[PDB]
Amino acid sequence: SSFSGKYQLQSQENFEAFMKAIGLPEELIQKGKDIKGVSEIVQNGKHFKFTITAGSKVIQNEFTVGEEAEMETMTGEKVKTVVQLEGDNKLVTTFKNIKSVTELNGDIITNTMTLGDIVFKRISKRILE
Amino acid sequence: SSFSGKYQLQSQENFEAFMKAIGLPEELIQKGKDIKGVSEIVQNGKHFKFTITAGSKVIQNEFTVGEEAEMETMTGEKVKTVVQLEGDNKLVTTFKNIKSVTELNGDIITNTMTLGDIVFKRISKRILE
Ligand SMILES: CCCCCCCCCCCCCCCC(=O)O
Ligand SMILES: CCCCCCCCCCCCCCCC(=O)O
Image (cartoon, rainbow over all chains, first blue to last red; front, side, top):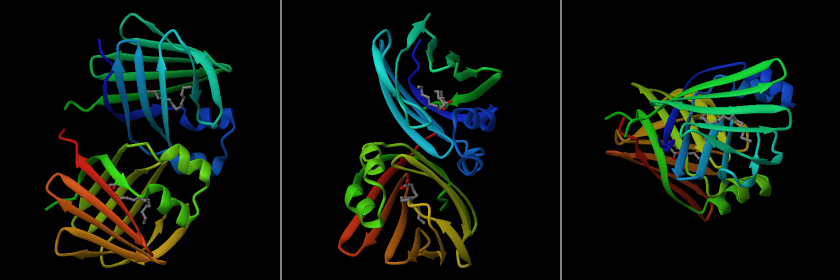
């Protein structure tokens, strides 16, 4: 019902392949590929504040679902996109050629980003505080 | 008696001045100055592993107190230094013209980095898992 929490990355698949596909340099990818950090979400109804840690980068994004917003991506590009809430537990959007689904089941977020044949999946667990 | 934990940045002083002094690109200073994320320490005796969130960057470092080590700074530069334990609750390192003191007070960690007349101070709080 609420996405709010601090989420510890537990495991991921295809980090290197996805970051290569979007244009990041190999040297940066290899430096970040094994980091398992903590991302944070604060949800207030349709409003979301994200402090995402992925690889060696921390990205802070904010949106209201259903409203267009500029989302900073791993390349540094700020993309214009609309994120929708499906049900109470799935955030969906598409930007460039990437389909993104952020799904909350209990205390586990599964984030799936699909770019052609590459399915980049991150599993993170809410720190219960 | 253990530094181990995940710590949420609560407040900080003179981020912009310190990052300017060490030469961080201005675009990264402006992006990173308001980000308050989670850093992790794993201590095993004199050995420490760090996953540090500072601004828009995540930095991993690892060393044994009392032994020379090579640590990655906020600019990405690698420096060789020996980290000491002071008074059983302070990690103290001096590299180039910076003195860094990481002090543990219960659930609070205070990182104080002194560079000439600038004191960059971070106060973080243990996440209770
Ligand atoms: C345009 C959207 C932002 C894209 C940023 C790319 C970094 C990977 C995104 C995964 C974060 C999704 C939130 C779940 C928590 C997590 O997996 O850290
Ligand atoms: C050897 C230099 C360390 C990395 C340089 C980044 C500047 C900030 C370092 C602060 C790390 C201290 C660890 C405790 C938690 C924190 O304050 O984030």
